[PDB]
Structures are given as structure tokens and as C-alpha cells.
Image (cartoon, rainbow, N blue to C red; front, side, top):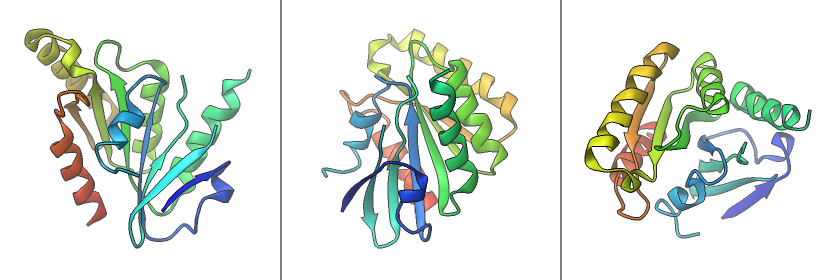
Length: 169
């Protein structure tokens, strides 16, 4: 099924396994999830009996509240087994992006960073950004895998499916 919940207290029973997706607006979150399924609020899609994908509201005096809710989810959700943080390869690692990774790492949650719109950069610049984010990510001291992603060219889709299969198994 497909569900939408107003807050964490309304999420379905905290049992089984789920993987969350997060990122600023226009990071390709929806487009990325569409490569996994064909099916503000927190949207959930159950891909199996007790296996769900969670789409956390984009974080793109008023934001303090919403940013706090994101951290509470990462810290309290017992069934959370991984976090996918999507960021545009042209402007990755913004303060909020780094905050989500740090929070995940402190809650012992594995992380997968997807540098989206990878097709927007030439081979040379694309590789340069990937290497930069990989080096930068070592500063978190966690389990942070980084991969380039392109919804248009369907690049990085298999890597995403493989990461998920590992976390779901």
C-alpha cells in the first residue's frame, strides 16, 4: 500500500524494517523513489510484508520545528535500518544535508548519499564531485556510502537497489 502520515506518532506500527529517504526540495527524491516503485507529510510505501520505504518531507524560526522532527524520527524509529540522503551533485553537502548524515551516524544508522542530477555534469567534473564528497564524508566516522545518481539516464539505480536489498535482508 501507499500511506501518508502527519507526524511520527501516526506512522504505522514500528515493527519490521524500513529505509528512509531525505533531501532538500528539487533533489530528485520523488524521481528516485519512482525508480524503486510504480505506486509536510511523511509518505510510506510498503514494498513487502514488514518492509517499508519512508519519504521524509524535504527540508528545503519556522524550520527549527521541522528539522527537529526529522532528528526525532532518526533517533526513535526502531525499525529504521538505513537512510538515503539525496543531494544535487552541483551543490551537495549543504548544512542541512550534513546534519541529517551526522544525526543518522550518531543513531547508528547506515547512510547512502546519492549525488543526483549526475548527468548534468561532464564525466570529469562528475568524478571530481564524487571524490570530493567521498573524502568529505569520512569526517563523520560512520557508515556513509556515496554514489552518483541519474533518474534520466537511470544511472545508479542498481546500486540503490543493491544497498536497499542489503538493508532489507
